[PDB]
Image (cartoon, coloured by chain):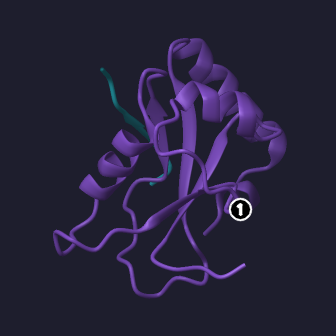
Amino acid sequence: EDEWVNVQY
Amino acid sequence: RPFKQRKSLAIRQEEVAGIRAKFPNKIPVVVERYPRETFLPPLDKTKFLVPQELTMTQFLSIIRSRMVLRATEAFYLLVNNKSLVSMSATMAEIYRDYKDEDGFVYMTYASQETF
């Protein structure tokens, strides 16, 4: 769907 | 459905810019399917935003997390679909070394590939 996967730490 | 063809360069740059402005601590990544692949299940998400302290090993697991697989079969994550890189390397290293023209880092997942 053309959108970000935001991962952290 | 490769990203470099979907989006024109300037658009990709704009995106990279806005998002690096949005999250100045994180690397922008594009993971795609090896077009010669037929065995593996497709990946639902296309763009990943990753910290710098993240290793390739961790990212691979995260990518695996988005897919339903038999807990054993692994696959290869090619950077620029041509680079087998150190499993221990951080996103920052991979970023500085293999930054594409538009600011993204491009990856490709394949169960098998021959060069």
Q: Nearer the viewer, residue B97 or B69?
A: B97
Against B61, is B53 above or below?
A: above
**On the picture, is B11 further left or further right than B46?**
right
Chain identifier, colour cyan? A
Give the amino acid at mark 1.
Lys
Chain bearing tag 1 is B
Against A6, is B17 above or below?
A: above
Label 1 sits on a secondary structure element that is loop
Q: Position of residue B109 (x, y in %)?
A: 50, 65
**Residue occupying image coordinates x 67% and y 38%:** B104
Q: Report the residue marked by disc 1.
A: B82
Q: Position of residue B111 (x, y in %)?
A: 45, 77
Quadrant housing residue B42 = bottom left
How many marks do you count on the picture?
Answer: 1
Q: Nearer the viewer, residue B65 or B15?
A: B65
Q: Which quadrant holds the C terminus of chain B?
A: bottom right
**On the picture, is B49 further left or further right than B29?**
left
**Residue occupying image coordinates x 31% and y 46%:** B62
Q: Position of residue B45 (x, y in %)?
A: 40, 54
The colour chain B appears in is purple
Q: Farthest left residue?
A: B71
Q: Nearer the viewer, residue B49 or B64?
A: B64
Quadrant housing residue A9 = top left
Q: Which quadrant holds the N terminus of chain B?
A: bottom right
Q: Farthest bottom residue?
A: B38
**Residue occupying image coordinates x 38% and y 50%:** B60
Q: What is the crowding at mark 1: few (fewer than 14 residues within 10 Å), some, or many (at least 20)?
A: few
Q: Position of residue B13 (x, y in %)?
A: 76, 33
**Residue occupying image coordinates x 57% and y 73%:** B34
Against B40, is A2 above or below?
A: above
